[PDB]
Structures are given as C-alpha cells and as structure tokens.
Amino acid sequence: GRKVYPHHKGLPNGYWSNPTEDRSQQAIQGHYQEYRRPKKDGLEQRDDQNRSVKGWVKPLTEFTFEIDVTNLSEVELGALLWLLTLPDLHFHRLGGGKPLGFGSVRLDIDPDKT
RNA sequence: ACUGAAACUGUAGUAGAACCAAUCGGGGUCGUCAAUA
Image (tube, rainbow, N blue to C red; front, side):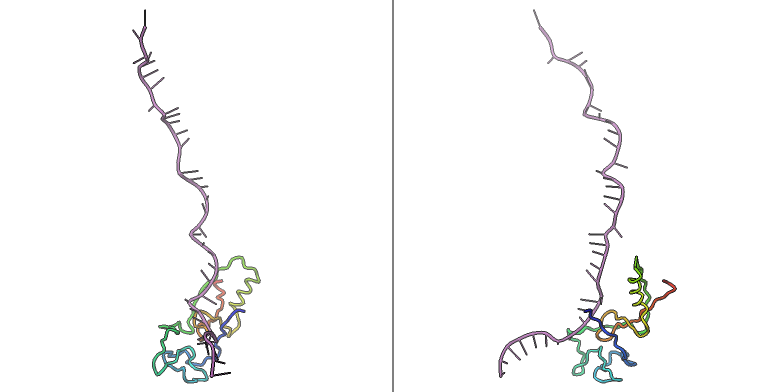
C-alpha cells in the first residue's frame, strides 16, 4: 500500500543542533546523528550518492497557508478537517529528507480566518 | 446606294459573435549487484 515515513519520535535535545558536527559516530542520548553523512578518514563524504544542503528551515518556524475548497461533501470535508485537527503529537511529513527525520510538521486550523 | 451616337456593373454592407491554454503531479528517496566453491 501507500508508503509513509513515520514521524521520528523521541529525537533528543540538540539532535538537529550544530549539524556540521559529525556526531554520527556517538550515541548522544541513544541516537546517532542519522541525518548526516558520516566522515570518512576525517574528511567529508560529499560523494555523488548524497546531496548537501546550504541550510534548512528551522524547527518551530511557522507558515500560514489557506485552502479554498469547492463543493466538498461532509465526508470529503470531514476527512480534510480531520487531517487539519489531529490530536497532539500527530505530525505530518513534508518536503524532502523524510527518511532522515526532516519535514515533520504540525498542521492546525486558524478558525478566525476560516 | 455608306459602321449610329452617348452610357463606370455600379450603389449600401466591420469576417464577425461566443469560447480561461487549461486539467493532474511533495524535487523525491535504500539494498541491491555479480555466481559459484
């Protein structure tokens, strides 16, 4: 069926912090720096199997967007609004790098603009 | 067993009215490959 990338629950404090540091080889709070290509012989493994990113959108940053909907039934609308009103600690997965933990996002409705 | 002459195929008339270059699509992501000893 439909392939999904489960949210990386329980990533410790500072997991994404200072990401240039090759912490991939130590179990800091029980997790390896799984999103970063490990260094080999002390040099960066910028091979043509991996990409590199000059930056990323920080965690806890916030985006607002709008959905304009037409002729949704109550089931079709209720399915949509369920996704946009999931209980706490349900997170959507967005963009790239999802296998590595990137792109976990919380969606919630702004009711005053709906 | 005396050539008729003279006479604009012209005048009026918008190739135009209606018609969305548009519909769908996360710049994304894991284990394969080779066959013998």
